[PDB]
Amino acid sequence: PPYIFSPIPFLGHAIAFGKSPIEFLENAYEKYGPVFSFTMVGKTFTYLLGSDAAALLFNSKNEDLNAEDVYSRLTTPVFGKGVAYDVPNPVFLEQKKMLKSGLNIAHFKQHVSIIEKETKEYFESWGESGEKNVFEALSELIILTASHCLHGKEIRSQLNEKVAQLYADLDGGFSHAAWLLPGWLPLPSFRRRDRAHREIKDIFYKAIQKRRQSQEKIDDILQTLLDATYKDGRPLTDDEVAGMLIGLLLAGQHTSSTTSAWMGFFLARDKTLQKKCYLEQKTVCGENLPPLTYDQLKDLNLLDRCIKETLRLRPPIMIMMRMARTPQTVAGYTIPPGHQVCVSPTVNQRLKDSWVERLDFNPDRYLQDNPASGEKFAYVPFGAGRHRCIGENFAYVQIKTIWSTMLRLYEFDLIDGYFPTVNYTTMIHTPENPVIRYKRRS
Amino acid sequence: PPYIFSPIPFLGHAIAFGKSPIEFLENAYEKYGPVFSFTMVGKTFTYLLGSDAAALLFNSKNEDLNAEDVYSRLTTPVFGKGVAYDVPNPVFLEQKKMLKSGLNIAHFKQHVSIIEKETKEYFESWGESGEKNVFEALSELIILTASHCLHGKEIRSQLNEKVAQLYADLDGGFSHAAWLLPGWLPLPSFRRRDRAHREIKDIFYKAIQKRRQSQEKIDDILQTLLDATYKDGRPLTDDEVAGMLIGLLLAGQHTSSTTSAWMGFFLARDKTLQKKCYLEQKTVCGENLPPLTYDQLKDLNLLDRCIKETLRLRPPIMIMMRMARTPQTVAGYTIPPGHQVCVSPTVNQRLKDSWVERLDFNPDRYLQDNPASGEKFAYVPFGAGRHRCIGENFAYVQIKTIWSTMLRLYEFDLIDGYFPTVNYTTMIHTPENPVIRYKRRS
Amino acid sequence: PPYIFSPIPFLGHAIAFGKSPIEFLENAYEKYGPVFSFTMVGKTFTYLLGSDAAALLFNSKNEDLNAEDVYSRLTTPVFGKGVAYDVPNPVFLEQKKMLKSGLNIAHFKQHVSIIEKETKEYFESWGESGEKNVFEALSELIILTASHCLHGKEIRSQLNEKVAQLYADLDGGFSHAAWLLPGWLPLPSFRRRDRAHREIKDIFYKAIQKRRQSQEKIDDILQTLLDATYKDGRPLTDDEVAGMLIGLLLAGQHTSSTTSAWMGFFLARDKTLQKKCYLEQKTVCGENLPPLTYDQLKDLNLLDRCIKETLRLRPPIMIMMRMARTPQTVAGYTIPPGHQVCVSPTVNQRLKDSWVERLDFNPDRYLQDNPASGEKFAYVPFGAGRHRCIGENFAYVQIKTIWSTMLRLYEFDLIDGYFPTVNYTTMIHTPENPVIRYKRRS
Amino acid sequence: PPYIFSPIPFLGHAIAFGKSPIEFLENAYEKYGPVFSFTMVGKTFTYLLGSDAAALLFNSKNEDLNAEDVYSRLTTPVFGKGVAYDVPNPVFLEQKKMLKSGLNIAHFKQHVSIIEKETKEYFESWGESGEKNVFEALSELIILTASHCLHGKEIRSQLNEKVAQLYADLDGGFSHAAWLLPGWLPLPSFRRRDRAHREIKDIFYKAIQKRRQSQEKIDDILQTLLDATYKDGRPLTDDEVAGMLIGLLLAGQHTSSTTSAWMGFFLARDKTLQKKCYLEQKTVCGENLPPLTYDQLKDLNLLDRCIKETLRLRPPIMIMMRMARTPQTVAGYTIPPGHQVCVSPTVNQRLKDSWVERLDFNPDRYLQDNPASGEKFAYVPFGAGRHRCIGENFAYVQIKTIWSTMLRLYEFDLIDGYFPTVNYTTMIHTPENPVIRYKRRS
Ligand code: HEM
Ligand code: HEM
Ligand code: HEM
Ligand code: HEM
Ligand SMILES: O=C(N[C@@H](Cn1ccnc1)c1ccc(-c2ccc(F)cc2)cc1F)c1ccc(-c2nnc(-c3ccccc3)o2)cc1
Ligand SMILES: O=C(N[C@@H](Cn1ccnc1)c1ccc(-c2ccc(F)cc2)cc1F)c1ccc(-c2nnc(-c3ccccc3)o2)cc1
């Protein structure tokens, strides 16, 4: 595959790529095509851009394009041993079926009123009007809603600011330092990550032992997990459950919070589209805006397309990476073992040749013919194939319910017309200076 | 000097020291005496503990024990060029005087009313009661109070969340990453630091030119700097002044916020003492508690001793360090060039030899024979000698005014008896989980 | 407990203790009594000498005096994950019961004829007379006998010089280097350990899979493991089984080889005794000396007492150690958490107070009153309590079968009256210059 | 010079280089050219690849590129005081001339018949055929031949298993632990080294005095040392002679044994070549293969080239290193003091640019134009300049004699076509699993 030369030793394209990766990759697509390699910080990466190329990653077996080889070093200290990329993929495929089994309609029905209430109670602190950081706000809110829904009421009631900070300490295990440096260096963020892991695990161990002795029946996701079994017939251990609960919260929080914050700003920019979203609430749920229900959520189809469009333009997982263990073919090229193969939903979901008015925020594009339905891997915010997301439905419930409630409470505006740029320096591309103006809804 | 061997290559005692640096130094004192050496992360350090040993550092000439050699590389990219450790010491000493001339009675009198107002207005958001993170609050207030007083009303008014983040980016330049790794690595913290430095220097350039061309006589710290002059007769360039303004704010924020936070918890744990600090407010300023004046602050003796005692047990600057350029002598040992010589106010200030009830918060210890007055270098939170603090006066005015105001507003308590342990992983040590219970002062 | 001062910082008494540990301990016993402490290498050790003091260690719960804390770091890379000190003690206790059920009379009956044949065949290479290193011979023979018996014929057949070297590479994981230095140094011994671990594991995985698939009923230790289940109901994984096989071989080899070597020299020195052992072979087994059977072993009483007395004077596991997790009281003292508590079989088994003619090799001492029967923890070559050995019976079958065969083959003598001194530079103390004179018996 | 950056603090490229040093250096050569630098375990190494660059090291004065500075620490405890890297280089140069005078034709003529006899006698144990470890056999054989030739018959008669172990203890002085850790630590290897040194010295002292007080005339290497003088007129002390005698054995053994073993396998792999070597024996010595003589060894040309080609592909001393004491210039670069400057015989002797079919074993490459005669430092298995070997002639006598003899006894083959890979974990690279098939020669 074509190789993009850089005269800068070791660093290669690091600076330019870090500054503007989408522009870097779109320029390369124009110049070298859908498949190309480059060096950055001592590693070779090979990209697959566009649906046809990306299909290799999305279709391939883990034995060929391996996820653990790239992610385990970073994730295993955060999520825990015996879970995710710390086990053989077939074990993780079973754990994912266990998790999926609890993300069902019965539970989603319960989650809606829990989330709505959590949201209304959080935003009382915003008062009738002002200008505040909506990203910080959603982050704090989403850690509460995710915990309430995915861990349950017992665990959620223990999530004070201390435990919230522990989760922030775990997050800090995902850094440039952790990627670049050996783990045996006693860096503060490493020690803080390991401390938080031990302390959260302990919180979960007690809660789990409590639940196991309890005589009561509780139909929640925790209970799905205590009841689950492998094809073996073997149940999950306390440590496996706890590892899974940590994963559920990290997965549940940052992908929803960034996406909810970008959509706030897309809707703040497009005031008519926001108005429409608010009017859809009256139409579907009634003029008197009663408590939200799951059945009503399915009927919020404009808000649905708005979320869908937010994920097109700002997918919170911007990249999917694998390690090539065996030789792989695409577009006539042969990628050898050792290349790290990458896909970028951001680049694919915005490619000129497939998306008309690619840079425009337009939810209604999905009511016409479009690459989301017309192609296989042009729209891939939740991935596809063996490593694909199991949380799309929950995420949509969480975000829909939060933004429905937020729309009912407030009208949102840009400050001096400013639309946030993308902060590329964070692992997750958050909107820069994400302060939003708000005032009471009519 | 006796060497504390570690068989661990490169790291040396890094892990044990990072976990509990104070306890590590106290144990070393008990086993090796007041002067000892060790390796940490590639480097040789020699400590001077106790008053008699520490004197070598405090009385030393910067030619012999050198500050720039150990600090320049980390500070120059934060504060700026031609300032602090980026210039020969004799030049920096003149800049300290320029700054000191501006930290005077007349200006302190203006600051009291300003700081008091900032404090009342910030703490409206807390309402009548609740449980909130006092450390975060004090950090947010103090950046305002420190800017209002040290920079001016004009620069202050421009201090929004965005610019406040710019300052945090600048704090982020003091990291292990920055200490360990080459500066040309495009790490996010490095870039943000360099970006934040240009954007702040620029906000200063604009206010520095506004003032020089204005006709209005304003008597403030900013003006003192603009008027000030070297022994040459040379005035300060815009960039010399701006860099000093940066230093001023970093010097004036977290030293006072951590300390202020700790005193909060010391007073929350000892209610009887808290009560007495409140009654002293009445007793000194009047039953009706009128606006504060600089004169009233000098008569707040119990409050003064609470601050002094907070600084004894939790000094924000845990270590002062120099590079030995010439052979030094102390307690019968000779320290060779290349060694880094260290003093710790924290250790000196709780040494078993010299402080009774050493770990107790007892502000009335200073009403009796004690090493603060009894010895020269046992109590040294603001250092001593050629490098000692010039902001001590302003720090007490800031902290006294805020906590006087805070005690008038609220009575503070612990949550479930918890006293914050020390977070050693932050540059300045911080209280862990520093959420405090508060309610309206009768 | 009384503390034994050393003026040598860091090392403390390590030199003297490395040279003459038994003498150090015996003199400390006389001077300080049965419980005392000292420092080496920044680590504080407390000894319990004599039956009454040792009782604390042997009787303690692992939650109080903990083996993992002191052994896990070295053993886990050797034996593998999920086994021995890498799991909570209760799981290891179940693992030990699985192993113990495999060490039964039906298997012992098979082992005697396996071991006799391996022994006759190995010693073909010794011819009619000569002078050779018995210790090397016993080590080479025992790795075959232990693998043949404990792993089975399939795995045994794959035990060539290459695999033997891999086991030596695993052994090399137990070193002063692995104890003293951190694991992230890429030392040759660590790399060879880790490679040997993967390569030995791989051999076991194939043999394990072979047997599961196979339809033939084989009654051997491997099969005991494949058929075993935890109280859980859960069977062992392939990796747990392989880990346990590695452990079986390492436990089965050096403990028997060193003891057998020592017994060789004790018998070479006391020719009258050696003759009596030879004649007991004729008396018990028959004048024509037919093949050994398991049932004759129990009637070989003199030989039994010879092994007992060799273990008395030369126990191959010369120390047992634990980390104190909770305060422990003995002899009026309180041992605090953090001390490593320590017993020596060697010292207990020769203490002047209880053993008459304590340094004499006198197998017949057990035919009158003696500390092994009259005291609880004076004779403890295989330990006692929760960490006690499961392999005593096997070791006696192995050693008796080998030495019965050797006595039938050869008469052994010393070389110019030399009796080997103890080599304290090896992990398990070996006899120095263990070359022995032999000639065809009768 | 270009620097190869590693983001791995301290360790630098330690792991990658230790895994595959030749591949590392050859890749570096391609990317950076003949001179480059990198960090490994806290040290800066600068390599000179190819003849023209390596010239700097081989042509350098010891005052500029110093050998004691890098080697002294490890070698002195092994060889003894007063010898080799423990004295200034001019003194060692004189000592080398003394050894040179001992390694003369009169002595070599004696050695051939000594070596042939030890060889025939040693391989008696091998029988008519089998599969045995040729590397271990050669190592054991060579310690005997080297000691018989270089120490004489008296000392050699005392070389039992015990003494051979003392020599292994000595070699054990050359460890990563001795490189990393202070000499005062009483580590096993340090203790065994120093004990072995004392005991071997005592064997040499008696033998030496035995000769000085004797009347017989013995023309052997010891006598040359005893009759030798410095320019001073000063003769060697007993400790100088004994130090040199240790050096002679350690240099004489492993360099020849590893090289001999590699050649076994090159010859077993290339049976046509092996047959030609056997036929050469008959051609030069005669059909009846009488006792070897020195004059015959000189005419065994094909065997000479097989050795030369073995040293080409597997030089036992893989690196030559010096401390830069003064700035040096090469390839338009300046190497500052403190850099460790290195040459790799293995890379030079394999370079893509110079050697056609670079990885082929082709002894006849030397009968055409080739870089061993066409360039100065492409072929340097024995070094060059002030530090070059004085043992090449003895080596060639020892190896030729042993293999001529082995070729007369046996034909050799690979086992299942396995060619030993390189074991990079040993000080001297060794062949992995060096068991070889052999059968009585026609
Ligand atoms: C808007 C919300 C979310 C987005 C955009 C998102 C995105 C993704 C993507 C792109 C992948 C594929 C990763 C890859 O191919 O390497 C993925 C996998 C996954 N996600 Fe999500 N996700 C979301 C929410 C959630 C939630 C709520 C959960 C759990 C409740 C979750 C759990 C997972 C899991 C378990 C995987 C599987 C990873 C693997 O098998 O390697 N996600 N997600
Ligand atoms: C509680 C508040 C503060 C504490 C505990 C504190 C402590 C110290 C200490 C210990 C030193 C000595 C550093 C050394 O010699 O290595 C010092 C120096 C200094 N402080 Fe502060 N300080 C505080 C507040 C301030 C403030 C508010 C300013 C300015 C407004 C300031 C400006 C300085 C300056 C300019 C130096 C001299 C640096 C040098 O000479 O190297 N400090 N401070
Ligand atoms: C002469 C031969 C042997 C001796 C002297 C010996 C000695 C010991 C001793 C003293 C302990 C207690 C360790 C402690 O408390 O820290 C022990 C434990 C043990 N031995 Fe042996 N042993 C021998 C042979 C074997 C054999 C043949 C096996 C297996 C077949 C074996 C397996 C074990 C196991 C599993 C433990 C348990 C360790 C623990 O629970 O922490 N041993 N042995
Ligand atoms: C195949 C066998 C041998 C090889 C490949 C070999 C290789 C070398 C090499 C490459 C050097 C240069 C060291 C440097 O420049 O850093 C050297 C030096 C030396 N060799 Fe050998 N050698 C061998 C056998 C011997 C023997 C048999 C002796 C003595 C009988 C010996 C004694 C020496 C001595 C004394 C030096 C001088 C070291 C110095 O001056 O720094 N070598 N050898
Ligand atoms: O090999 C170890 N223990 C042995 C003790 N043993 C042998 C026979 N009966 C008991 C061992 C323990 C458990 C097992 C084992 C356990 C479970 C199983 F299924 C199979 C085997 C096998 C063993 F060989 C071992 C080795 C070294 C150390 C060690 N810890 N610290 C050091 C140390 C300290 C200072 C300097 C050098 C080494 O060494 C601890 C344990
Ligand atoms: O044994 C060493 N050198 C050998 C090199 N040699 C062998 C044959 N021809 C030359 C050597 C050098 C001088 C002599 C010698 C000296 C004097 C004399 F009278 C006779 C012989 C003998 C030798 F064996 C030696 C070994 C190790 C090291 C060493 N330096 N660093 C390391 C090292 C570094 C990192 C990790 C581990 C080891 O190892 C340096 C020299």
Image (cartoon, coloured by chain):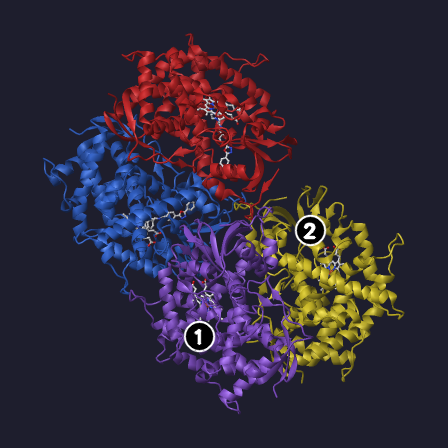
Chain colours: A purple, B yellow, C blue, D red
**Along the line of sight, which residue is nearer the eye, D396 or C232?**
D396
Quadrant of the snapshot with the C terminus of chain A: bottom right
Q: Residue at x 14, y 47 (%)?
A: C295
Residue D330 % position (x, y):
62, 31
* Chain where mark 2 sits: B
The Cα–Cα distance between marks 1 and 2, rounded to whole angstroms, is 51 Å
> Which dot marks residue A393?
1
* Chain where mark 1 sits: A
How many labels, in total? 2
Residue A83 shows in the view: no
Q: Which amino acid lies under the numbered mark 2 shown in the image of this protein?
A: Arg
Residue A293 % position (x, y):
46, 85
What element does badge 1 sit on? helix
Residue that numbered label 2 is attached to: B73
Q: Quadrant of residue B215?
A: bottom right
Q: Which amino acid lies under the numbered mark 1 shown in the image of this protein?
A: Asn
Q: Residues within 10 Å of mark 2 (few under 14, many from 20)?
A: some
- Determine contact: label 1, label 2, CB under 8 Å: no
Residue D382 % position (x, y):
49, 24
What element does badge 2 sit on? helix
B62 shown above or below B161: above
